[PDB]
Image: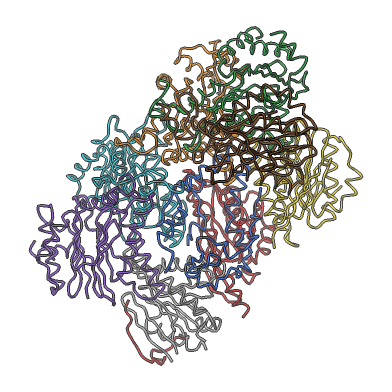
Amino acid sequence: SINGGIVVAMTGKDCVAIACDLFEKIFHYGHVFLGITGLATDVTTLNEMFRYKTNLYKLKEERAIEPETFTQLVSSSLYERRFGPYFVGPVVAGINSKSGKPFIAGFDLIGCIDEAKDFIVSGTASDQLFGMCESLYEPNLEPEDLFETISQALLNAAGAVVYIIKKDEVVKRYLK
Amino acid sequence: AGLSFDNYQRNNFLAENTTIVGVKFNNGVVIAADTRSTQGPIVADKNCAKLHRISPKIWCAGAGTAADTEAVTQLIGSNIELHSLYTSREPRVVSALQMLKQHLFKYQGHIGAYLIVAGVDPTGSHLFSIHAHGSTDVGYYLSLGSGSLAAMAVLESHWKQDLTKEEAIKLASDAIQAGIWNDLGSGSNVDVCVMEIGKDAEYLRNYLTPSYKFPRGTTAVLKESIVNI
Amino acid sequence: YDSRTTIFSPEGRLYQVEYALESISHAGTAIGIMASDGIVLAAERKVTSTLLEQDTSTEKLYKLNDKIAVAVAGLTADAEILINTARIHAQNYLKTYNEDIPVEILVRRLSDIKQGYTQHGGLRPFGVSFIYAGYDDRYGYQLYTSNPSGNYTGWKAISVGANTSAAQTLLQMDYKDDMKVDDAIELALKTLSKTTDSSALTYDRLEFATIRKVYQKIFKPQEIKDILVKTGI
Amino acid sequence: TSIGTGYDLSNSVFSPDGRNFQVEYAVKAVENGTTSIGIKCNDGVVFAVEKKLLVPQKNVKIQVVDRHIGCVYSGLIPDGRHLVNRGREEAASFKKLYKTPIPIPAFADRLGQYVQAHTLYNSVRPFGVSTIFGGVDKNGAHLYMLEPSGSYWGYKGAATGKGRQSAKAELEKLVDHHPLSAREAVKQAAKIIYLELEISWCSLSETNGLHKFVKGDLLQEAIDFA
Amino acid sequence: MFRNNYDGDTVTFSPTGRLFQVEYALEAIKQGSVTVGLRSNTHAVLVALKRNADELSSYQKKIIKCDEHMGLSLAGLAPDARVLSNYLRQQCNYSSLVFNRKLAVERAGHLLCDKAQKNTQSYGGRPYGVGLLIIGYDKSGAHLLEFQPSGNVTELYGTAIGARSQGAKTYLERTLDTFIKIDGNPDELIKAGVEAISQSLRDESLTVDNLSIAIVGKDTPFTIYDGEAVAKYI
Amino acid sequence: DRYSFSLTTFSPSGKLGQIDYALTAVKQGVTSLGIKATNGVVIATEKKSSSPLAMSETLSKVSLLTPDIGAVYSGMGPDYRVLVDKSRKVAHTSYKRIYGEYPPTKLLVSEVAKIMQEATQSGGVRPFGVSLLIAGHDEFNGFSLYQVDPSGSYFPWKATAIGKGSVAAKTFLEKRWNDELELEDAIHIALLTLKESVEGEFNGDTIELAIIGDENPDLLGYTGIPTDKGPRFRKLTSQEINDRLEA
Amino acid sequence: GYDRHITIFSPEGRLYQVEYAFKATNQTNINSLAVRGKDCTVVISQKKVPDKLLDPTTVSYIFCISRTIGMVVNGPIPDARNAALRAKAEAAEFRYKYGYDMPCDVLAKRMANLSQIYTQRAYMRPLGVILTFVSVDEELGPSIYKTDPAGYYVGYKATATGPKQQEITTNLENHFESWEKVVEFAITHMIDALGTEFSKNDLEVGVATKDKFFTLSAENIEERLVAIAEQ
Amino acid sequence: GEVSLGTSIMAVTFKDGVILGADSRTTTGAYIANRVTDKLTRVHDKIWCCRSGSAADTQAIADIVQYHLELYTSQYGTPSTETAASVFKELCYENKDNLTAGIIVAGYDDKNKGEVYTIPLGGSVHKLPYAIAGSGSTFIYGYCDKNFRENMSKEETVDFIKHSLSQAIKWDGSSGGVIRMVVLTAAGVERLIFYPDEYEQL
Amino acid sequence: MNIVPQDTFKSQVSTDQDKSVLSSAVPSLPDTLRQQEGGAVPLSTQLNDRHPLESTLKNWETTQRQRQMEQYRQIFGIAEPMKRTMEMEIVNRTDFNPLSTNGSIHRDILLNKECSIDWEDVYPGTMVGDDVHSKIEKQLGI
């Protein structure tokens, strides 16, 4: 089944990583990347909704949404369906265009914000990957050391894709 | 309009398939909380900041459904901001208490936010608790969360009338430490906010704070591509 | 008979809508030109003065979508109400079909909106006419206009506002449908330069855009000035 | 200027002098009605009016709104009937709520608010009636006259209708003579009307504080006095 | 002249307080055909001269029945007569259904008074322009009410409404001393009514088609006599 | 009664009469002006009072819309007050409650313009008889100044003035404005323009002036969140205004 | 045209129907005064009752709106009583919603916004009254706010209202321990401005104190007048 | 798990007026969430009530009553205690299916000179010389019924309320803390408080 | 005199209860194309197992308003609720705007919601029947 699976995001120096075990579950709205686990119907509905919202944002503001503002947009859009939520675990990752601050966040079904600075995991096998990330992770990884850390952690969580995000470029990679 | 119900029957069918304290003192009130956050047995985030601001001198901390406490706290902070602008007056803590309890009452307890609201206003310092059903009680000291019993034990052992600012901060941080040590849900750092009747509120983030990297090339890259945006 | 938009006159004509049409005769001229390889949009900034922020007064050309832009003549408040309605419609269409809205469907929706305000008595017509430039993979590059009456027409080149008759005569003499975008830019600039009531077509009095290649660009005043001096105005 | 052409053909319009000419015309409607007086005693109040196939025991002009409070109106019959019935509803609801007779000032307030509300919108017209009402009360007895504007005041005596001016003058002379018993006030009301008769009164001593009709022997004695 | 300015609606008074728009609805009764009503103490009788539009047409039904105790007579606007009759009969019914009590005639009249008053004060509608005579018999005995579309109701021993009602009403004013005593002999009260309605006739005479009668009393539910049943009284 | 005819309509000339008459009501209003500096914006106006017994401290013609955005008006004060209330409410509801941050000045101006425009379509209300100068700062658009007219049209300005003095003030600004002003220079030019525009007594109690500038942490009311930003809107006290006038 | 019957703009940019609603406020000849002490606010109104038949007990234009707020109305009594009921309901609703006693200026702001509604809806006439609210606020102390039919309001150090309001205002400008002294001061200045030596029933007086608002009774106005006549 | 006002509350009419007394414990199960809560709620200057049942529904009801009665007072002057009891009755009854509230209303009123109304969970209203309610009242029905007397003095009524509430506190776990009382008389409102060391040694 | 909305369930149901969306061919059944609800499949019988809160949260404000009018009737009499309601209906009936979702600026003042936010404000939340003409026809009752 294509429902569920796992998404993880992780912070480096001047970079972030986001990865999932794969239909697709990582989306991007300009320079802000949203990973969503859960029901694939709800993943698709969230993708359509946040595409709508961020297109209207970009049209009204003449400006691409910043990851912190997109995080607040995701939070408020999830809470709107406080009763009968989407069965999803979204994760946002990105870098602020002005400050270059690498940013990650993750949410519950109703948009509580973790905003943890080190790493965020969601979905199936979350406690296994929490243990992996805690053990493997070290702060201030280089972009390629960050790639190795995220990709190895994901492979040991249980066919994967990795985005390495710089301020000015993004590298997309795949894993068996 | 409002909070949607539009997947209630759907999600039903599919399902068929912390320590916080407030401490009033001789010229103010101290509110403090731990900074652990947990999902199930798992620490989702250490150093989570649990002290919310309703107004410059009205601050809040909550238990129950975190998203609910956040949403209601930011709604009431918006209403308090707008009312202060409308009346050109520094907002009263009794006004926040009133509108917060009337909001929670409107939702008949289905919005599961339990809160301690502390502040100073032109009429003095105030400290209140609010329950998700919309029931309130005033106090001179309060505790909330899974560690509420340990913190209340400390407050009741050491609280006294006419605490000073420093003695009140000490008492509050001792009660949070007792929570951290005795409750599993509490842990990591202690946050404190100090409101004095004549003074700017003094927020004190983390007032108390009680290799395996693999070599490059380890992971089997399958292929590469450039995504541009 | 003219007191309200819901009353036919004895001649069978809706004076209130003819007055909404006449309102545009006082808006600065907008012009649009469709080329073999793109579309040009240009407009006069008739409301101008040295204390106005020309660099941020994007005030007649508005993108509604990727691959679609509008040029506005008439009441800017009504213009931005309709622009935001059209943006919402285009995003609803993309959300529903996962395809970019066809330009004609958007023009039709906006013209039906403008028409309805002519038919209920508590509403006045919108005192605004749009030129629509866009691209879709059904009809390719296509260019439209619509009136306060809520009728619309497809055009290869069109002018709206004060001196529309003169501009359209100059287009009818000079336009040829195998010209390129770089040719259409210069034909637009020539037309506006001969049409404007100003002593000279200074770059601050212009707003300019093109849809070509699919990408759209709204020119900043620097490249507007460069395109002007390249044309020789 | 009494006509106000150009500011009169619609309700709620202020003229340039701030006058609401539709209200002045509704006042002028009252000036056509049956001359009616009320008199306030030391102990109570009394009302009198100047007024063949009609059933005579059913042809009555003074309206008891409640046993507590008596009412008489002049001007448009249907407007008077409507205002009377609205007041009787307000009295009955007050009594149901607070288990006490409606204080005469509270009743007066409610009626003034109801009439005044008809001055706010072009979709309604002012009542074409001026009402005199009053009764014994917890605080004594009160006499009010409610103009079609919704303006009302307490009075020691009031008169409305075509004869209102002479009635006012004689009732003012009466007040100047007594700076009254229910009996004497009844006699003077009969006189003022004579200057068919129907009278009613409300006093603590002589009607137990209820409103009652003055009929039979005392009516004939009042006619003899007149 | 100046009346033309202040007569456009029920919501403008004139500079003289007239409220012309209600006066015009009271004049609308004068366009109606004559009907007479009278009662004794034990019985109440209505008499009506019906009309027809053309010799090829039937006569219009001018009298109605709220229930077995009360009934009604119409003069004036047919649409408003229809409205008010339906209203009076829906009140008679609701009263019976909820309380199982015959609606008092006086109460029914007051209900009509109230309904009629509303249209005199709101802008959008118009006054009902129709007069009604109500008769009934209840615990309080025989009743006759005259309703005017100004929203005025009077209980009377006898009256007439319609174009020449003044003649019949003058006749009744001369003779009320006689008909009110007619107790237990209703035939003489009916014949007195037909006599009263024999005044105010013009170029016409009472006939079994054009004349209609009804009666109610202590021993007699509301019955309508029309056609050959009227020949007993012509 | 289900419909009410449009109160604002086009004249045969194509001009919407009520819009012209609202702009005339604006022209009748007391002078107000605003000036972009490189490092701030000034907005200023006369506190005309109907009596010396009125409390000038209650004649709040300049009002905060957001910590970074402020407004002033000329014309019908009650309309301005209702528009301020609605603009604050919409700044919270539409934007702060969705994105967790205050709107940029451009979008709050657009929201006010939308609110003002719809009074021009309704058949129940007249248009608002005010034009607003809205000055603000945005993290990306920087300092900005917009003039909103009764039509709900708005344009960005370097400097502008509205009301009785509007034309003479705009000429004085056009001769005196330059792209290098500091906020103290803009404040001086504003005060000189208003001195030239005001009628009668010109003092720190007959004027009020607000600025958009750097953050004021002493106006934030709390300490200890170092990323958190003091308000950039600041009304000058009449003491400070008098200390400017002594220059 | 329509600008005469409804509150739309005239070509001058003027709402004639609101200006005419201002002229309605002087259709009664009463004039009134409000002044502030250190810790009290006093409002003086004339009570013109020449009609022998009229009972001056009932003739009051001063309304107690809240425990701590009173207002005097200038203009026709029906609209004054309407405004009174409106303000009173709004003060009670504010207390219910926000948990503290409504400030005088917040009530003034509310009533001014309502008047703006009436100045902007075509089908609602302006109310035709000027409202002067007096209170002792717990933050601002004694304060006076006056509200116009236009929906303008401003705070005042003192006010006058009615046909002669300029004379009183100018007398106050000429001028500029317990509330009884402030009442006597205000009465003395009313006398000096208007030139009428008041009878005990020619006046009505309202006092806002730190704790409550109250109206003087005729025997209290009598003793105030006596205490004036001692000087 | 809503907060319920586990309570012992007791109002007693006496020669000069009425005294309304309460404990000050409130409990969430076995936990005392507040041990010095003030259960006495002023709805008007001389009209006071005590609340039982859920804290949220009773607080909402009492706030709506205080609104209604302030509006009334602004229109008609001071209400009678019977008016207040009527408002309480109407709110408790028309919401009886949704809200669980029981109220003792006590108030002084110069025409009636002090009255007590109890509104049990059903929304009946009963005027009584004294009323007891809450968990702890059950243990003191016999004491109050034996020891109550009509037209007690103030001091005798204070003693009586102290002895009753002290026994309720003794036997009921859900009630305790300090005893709080308001004395309502023509002289004014007087707050009283009695501490455990002042009532346990009885 | 209600706090929580009591009357909150439809007492009677019919295929014709929903007006303005009826089949022109057979004026007894819904128009499932014009409903645009995803077919007939939202059959009216599926109005079952509603969230317990929904039926109270939808009409909470209406209930508060009705209680407020009742209180004004009890204390001030029939004049005050009548005045309030007439004002409110004037505002509602004169504000026609088919393009704006936003609430009227004067409606908020009358409701005393000038300085209040609720989730209905924050979260104000189609191939057929969305057109301006459908709104015109609803509003005029065409």
Q: Image point 30% across, 70% down: which residue?
A: C103
How is the protein colored in the picture?
by chain
Q: Nearer the viewer, residue B200 or I13?
A: I13
Q: Is residue F33 visible?
A: yes
Q: Which chain is orange?
A: G
Question: Does A98 sit left or right of C163 as displayed?
Answer: right
Question: Whole-percent x and y of residue A34?
Answer: 43, 75
Question: Whole-percent x and y of residue I46?
Answer: 60, 70
Q: Is residue H153 above or below residue H56?
A: above
Q: Which chain is red?
A: B
Question: Whole-percent x and y of residue E90?
Answer: 66, 46
What is the drawing colour of chain I? Answer: blue
Furthest residue to the left? C232
Q: Quadrant of residue F150?
A: top left
Question: Whole-percent x and y of residue I65?
Answer: 58, 48
Q: Is residue D106 visible?
A: no
Q: Image point 55% across, 59% down: which residue?
A: B72
Q: Nearer the viewer, residue F214 or H51?
A: H51
What is the drawing colour of chain C? Answer: purple
Question: Does C85 sit left or right of A135 as displayed?
Answer: left
Q: Quadrant of residue E5?
A: top left
What is the drawing colour of chain E? Answer: brown
Counting labels gives: 0
Work out which quarter of the rendered image holds the C terminus of chain B and state it. Answer: bottom left
Furthest residue to the right? H146
Q: Is residue B166 above or below residue D87?
A: below
Q: Which chain is cyan?
A: F
What is the drawing colour of chain D? Answer: green
Q: Nearer the viewer, residue G116 or G132?
A: G116
Q: Quadrant of residue D42?
A: top right
Q: Is residue G117 above or below residue B188?
A: above
What is the drawing colour of chain H? Answer: yellow
